[PDB]
Structures are given as C-alpha cells and as structure tokens.
Length: 155
Length: 141
Image (tube, rainbow over all chains, first blue to last red; front, side):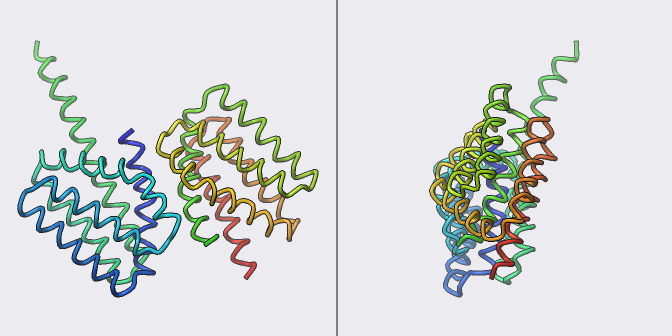
C-alpha cells in the first residue's frame, strides 16, 4: 500500500533526521547542502522527474549521514518502493503547483535543523513535513469524492 | 550498535502492534496466543536460548498478523540483526533475573491489547515495553 509506506517513512525518516543532526561530519553536512540545493534547481526548471530524483538522493545522503547501520539497511531494503512513493507524491504535487513551495519549505526546516545540529527539531520537522504531504493527498481524495458526489446529487 | 537497533524496533514494533490489533483474524490471534504462552514456558524452564527464540517467533507472528506488506519486508530485511538483538538483550536480562517478570509483564500488556483489538493501547504498550528495555541497557554501563 502507498498508505502503509508513508507511515513507515514517517517513522524511519524522523529517526534518520535525528541521528543525522547528531552524527553528521563536516563533509556530510556539505554533501547534503549540495543535494538540498539541487532540489531547488530541479523545482525551478519545472522538471518533475529531476526533482523527484533530487529528493531521493537527498534522503539517502541524510540517512548515510546518520551513521546508523540498521537504518541505512532498511532504506536500501525499501529503496525501490521509496523511489516510487516520492515519484507518485510529486505527480500529485505537480497537479497543484502552488503547494510545491510549501513542501520544500517544510523539508528546508529539517535540513536547517540538521546543519544546526538540533536533533529534536530535526525529527519534529520531518514528522510535520510528511504529515503535511499526507494531508495534501487526502484533500485530493476528498475533493475528487465531492466532485462525483456533488455533480451526481444535482438531479 | 545494540542501542540504535532498539530505537528502530521501538518505531517499527509499535506500528506492528497497532495494525496487528486492527487487522488480526481469529486464526492469527490464536497462533499468537500459543506463541505468547510458549515464552512463559521457556522462561519458567530457565532456558535463555529457548526464550530468546520464543520471543523472535512471537514478534514475527505479530508482524504477519498486521497484514502490512512493508513492515513484514522490513522485519525480514533486519531479521538476522533482530534475532541477535533479542538474544543479547536476554543475556543482559538473565544477569538480573528480577527484571524478567517485569519485561514479560510489559510484553503481555501488548498481547492483551492485540487480542482485545485496541490499537492505540497496543502501540503505547510496545513503546513502554521497549523503552523499559532501553532503560535497563543504559543502567548496565
């Protein structure tokens, strides 16, 4: 399920961000800065597949920067489904382009908390980032449900 | 380490218990009851390796009973390290035998919440169960 997977990323990306904040070296923090900025460039060029891959690579670097053997192993284990989930999320976000900045905004609060070495904040930022995506997905479902329900109820 | 792994189970076993409570069939709940009782028998015989395997099998059944494809995939993925973590935890618990009953006690609140079909209680029970183990590990060194 694409639903069950989000709840799992919710859990695992939070802890990833936590340890990344606490254990990232100076080289890690720099390699992450370039990957975070790569997301912005892909978003401004308006290329969905480019931005989707930029996010996947960012999240991998964050996980490696966490230096937690089991977490990295779990990411690699689900990497194909994760890559698919991010791609699907962005297909729905590119439908409502006004949300993209707000999503990147949430993701940037995680990045900034990692660079700053604040674990608690980084984890809470990740929860809110993914929680906010779940909310956008549910609004698509809700409005498309009203769509049919309302246009059918008129007579 | 043994520490990082606990935080990972903390997360994943909570969600496992949640869905197990919500989605377990009658056959699942029964297969889990036999595995839970098997832990008690292994504990009373005082056999560490037997009780360690009983817990591993219990947790697998709980995960399967959750009917959540990604969770099961993640368990299988880390199964070797998980089996090792449980075995190591019990080596430290068998050092302070007075804790064993309290650990089984916490784990039984999860089981009971699953049989009863109460997801939020089952998840909260799992957090307290593993949180309590993390505390015992930190007191060791």
